[PDB]
Picture 1 (cartoon, chains in turn brown, yellow):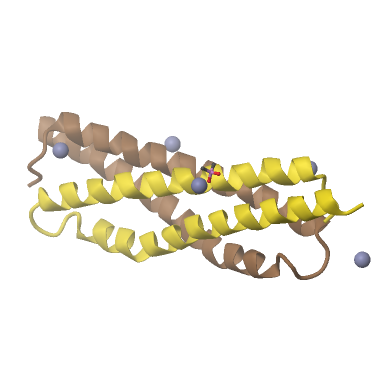
Picture 2 (tube, protein in one colour):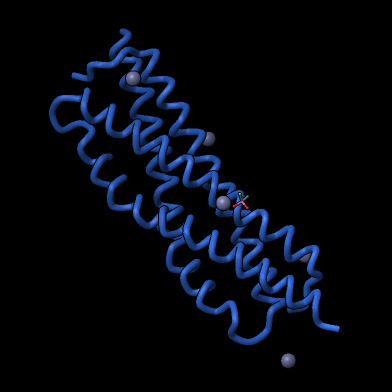
Length: 83
Length: 84
Ligand SMILES: C[As](C)(=O)[O-]
Ligand SMILES: [Zn+2]
Ligand SMILES: [Zn+2]
Ligand SMILES: [Zn+2]
Ligand SMILES: [Zn+2]
Ligand SMILES: [Zn+2]
């Protein structure tokens, strides 16, 4: 099926899992920062950036979730290849 | 803005660092996707490739947005610091 060694598959899996975790943490931190900025900057100057952040955030979340699913699949596949 | 220039710049740094980290993850994982896809015959990985490709441009746009916010914040901090 897959022509890659278990050892390399597991290294890839760590990259996907670590990427997922880091993207979730960045989105959490910057979501907090957006809130603090938006609340302390009255009026409209930052509004275009807020609108784009809100539109893109759910996609970034979706991407982190995908990465976690790829991690799980690669773990499974490494097991099967090795066994 | 009701925030000190120093705090505005601390936040700016976080947006920049986040952007850099996301672009690094995206570059690394795009290379992984290609290698895994190339070495997996049949349809098993196809759905993950499809979903990755659908979302990656939006993640790239998000990284770009964070750099734009970083520079907007820097410029705003400069203006606050100049306002007597
Ligand atoms: C190199 As940077 C942390 O200013 O985007
Ligand atoms: Zn390799
Ligand atoms: Zn994790
Ligand atoms: Zn604060
Ligand atoms: Zn006012
Ligand atoms: Zn940067």
